[PDB]
Image (cartoon, rainbow, N blue to C red):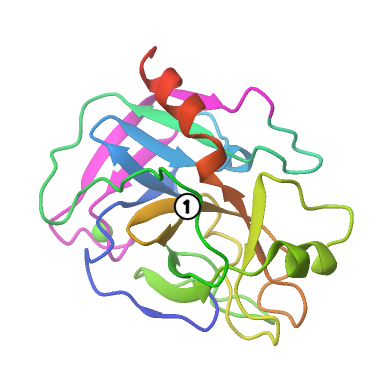
């Protein structure tokens, strides 16, 4: 997250870190057994880390739980990032508590202009590289579809939305991928892509989770 703030330990209690020997992507806990992330974060051998603040220090509230299954969307296209969503099942149910909690899925899609909370352990620099140890947060508005299409002509599908600041300076970034965009208490986006980070006229692009609620529900009903 570039231009964000330190969230505060365990105040984003649905935020997970996906670990394959190191943090490589975020995700969102949607119930005791399941995490939503980005399909472009797929790796074999994922350990889900819940209750994290500093990902390099054991602080006492973590639950580390292996993935048993990952399910990339049937229509994910890695070339265009359309349908950039993945489900990850945990080998055992998380113990839900004040610091490890699920985030609601949406019923309706989010409104343009809504200020959402984006979080992660990704790069904090627009030019160069610095990865934080503690979880970072950013408040960012959903941009209009017209504005998003203008920014990335030919590349925005109905399953994507843009959010952030066209003047630059505030965005998600590498390593935030797969983590949450929460709007009105619902998981409405997944950190997906963007040209660079926090560059002028190049806002973040996010998977539009409200297009996936029927696939998420039938998949979890079946696995
Ligand atoms: Ca930790």
Q: Confirm whether the magenta stretch covers residue 202.
A: no
Q: Is mark 1 within 8 Å of ligand 1?
A: no
Left or right: residue 198 versus residue 101 is right
The image quadrant where one finds ligand 1 is bottom left
Q: Residues within 10 Å of mark 1 (few under 14, many from 20)?
A: many
Left or right: residue 217 versus residue 64 is right
x and y percent of residue 16 in the render?
35, 50
x and y percent of residue 2 in the render?
55, 78
Q: Confirm whether the magenta stretch covers residue 47.
A: yes
What residue is drawn where x is 55% and y is 72%?
113
Q: Is residue 45 visible?
A: no
Q: Quadrant of the C terminus?
A: top left
Q: Is residue 183 visible?
A: yes
Task: Write the start and end of the magenta stretch as one range.
Answer: 46-75
x and y percent of residue 23 in the render?
45, 52
Front position in the image: 95 or 175? 95
Kindly indicate the quadrant of the structure image that contains residue 135. bottom left
Q: How many marks?
A: 1
Q: Determine the secondary structure under disc 1.
A: strand
What residue is drawn where x is 10% and y is 48%?
97
What residue is drawn where x is 54% and y is 59%?
175
**In the rendered image, the vertical position of residue 193 relative to residue 41, given as above or below:** below
Front position in the image: 29 or 63? 29
Q: Residue furthest top?
A: 222
What residue is drawn where x is 65% and y is 80%?
126
**In the rendered image, the vertical position of residue 172 relative to residue 104, given as above or below:** below
Residue under label 1, please give it. 188
**In the rendered image, the vertical position of residue 170 relative to residue 202, given as above or below:** below
Q: Residue furthest right?
A: 154
Kindly indicate the quadrant of the structure image that contains residue 163. bottom right
């Amino acid at each position: 997250i570039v231009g964000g703030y330190t969230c505060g330990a365990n105040t984003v209690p649905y935020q997970v870190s996906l670990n394959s020997g190191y943090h490589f992507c975020g995700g969102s806990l949607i119930n005791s057994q399941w995490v939503v992330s980005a399909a472009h974060c797929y790796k074999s051998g994922i350990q889900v880390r819940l209750g994290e603040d500093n990902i390099n220090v054991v602080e006492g509230n973590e639950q580390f739980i292996s993935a048993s299954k990952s399910i990339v969307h049937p229509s994910y296209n890695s070339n265009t990032l359309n349908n950039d969503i993945m489900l990850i099942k945990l080998k055992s149910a998380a113990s839900l508590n004040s610091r490890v909690a699920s985030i609601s899925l949406p019923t309706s899609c989010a409104s343009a202009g809504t200020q959402c909370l984006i979080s992660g352990w990704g790069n904090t620099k627009s030019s160069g590289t610095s990865y934080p140890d503690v979880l970072k947060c950013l408040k960012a508005p959903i941009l209009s579809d017209s504005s998003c299409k203008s920014a990335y002509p030919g590349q925005i599908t109905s399953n994507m939305f843009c959010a952030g600041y066209l003047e630059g300076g505030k965005d998600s970034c590498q390593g935030d991928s797969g983590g949450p965009v929460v709007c009105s208490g619902k998981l409405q986006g997944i950190v997906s892509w963007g040209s660079g980070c926090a560059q002028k006229n190049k806002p973040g692009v996010y998977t539009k989770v409200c297009n996936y609620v029927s696939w998420i529900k039938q998949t979890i009903a079946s696995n």
